[PDB]
Image (cartoon, rainbow, N blue to C red):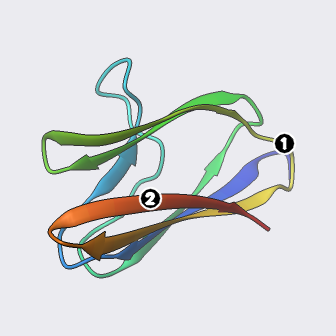
Amino acid sequence: KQKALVRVQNLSGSKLTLKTADGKTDVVKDVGPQSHGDREINPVKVNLALFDGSKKVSDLKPVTLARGEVVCLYVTGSGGKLAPVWVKR
């Protein structure tokens, strides 16, 4: 493929989304509570950040994507807080 495969894995008990911190533009679509979502994204620098509803949780920062690259963000829940762990496959 000519795009990178990016997944968001919600391992928490709260709805969250992967979007940018430079605007309202998102990164991965179709992500809800206790679930996951996929999105094919151009092989460019993409600003990653974890939001819970309208609340900014963590700034994961710009990452470099490549064609055919498969990655997945694993966000766990603990103590009422979220712990995003970005994993490359």
Which one is in front, 76 or 47?
76
Residue type at mark 2 is Pro
Label 2: few (<14), some (14–19) or many (≥20) C-alpha neighbours in 10 Å: many
Question: Can you say whether 56 is above or below 83 in the image?
Answer: above
Label 1: few (<14), some (14–19) or many (≥20) C-alpha neighbours in 10 Å: some
Q: Quadrant of the C terminus?
A: bottom right
Task: Count numbered badges in the picture.
Answer: 2
> Position of 56 compared to 27: left or right?
left
Where disc 2 sits, the SS reads strand
Which one is in front, 80 or 26?
80
Which mark sits nearer the N-terminus, 1 or 2? 1
Question: Can you say whether 43 is above or below 23 in the image?
Answer: below
| Residue depicted at 38% across the width and 61% down the height | 83
The x and y percentages for residue 57 are 26, 44
The part of the image, by quadrant, that contains residue 30 is bottom left
| Residue depicted at 28% across the width and 73% down the height | 77
| Residue depicted at 26% across the width and 59% down the height | 16
> Position of 25 compared to 78: left or right?
right
Where disc 1 sits, the SS reads loop
Q: Please give the label number shown on residue 84.
A: 2
Question: Can you say whether 66 is above or below 28 in the image?
Answer: above
| Residue depicted at 37% across the width and 29% down the height | 25
Residue type at mark 1 is Ala
Q: What residue is pinned by disc 1?
A: 66
Q: Please give the label number shown on residue 74.
A: none
1 vs 2, front mark: 2
The x and y percentages for residue 5 are 70, 58
Q: Quadrant of the N terminus?
A: bottom right
Which residue ends up furthest to the front in the rendered image? Answer: 79
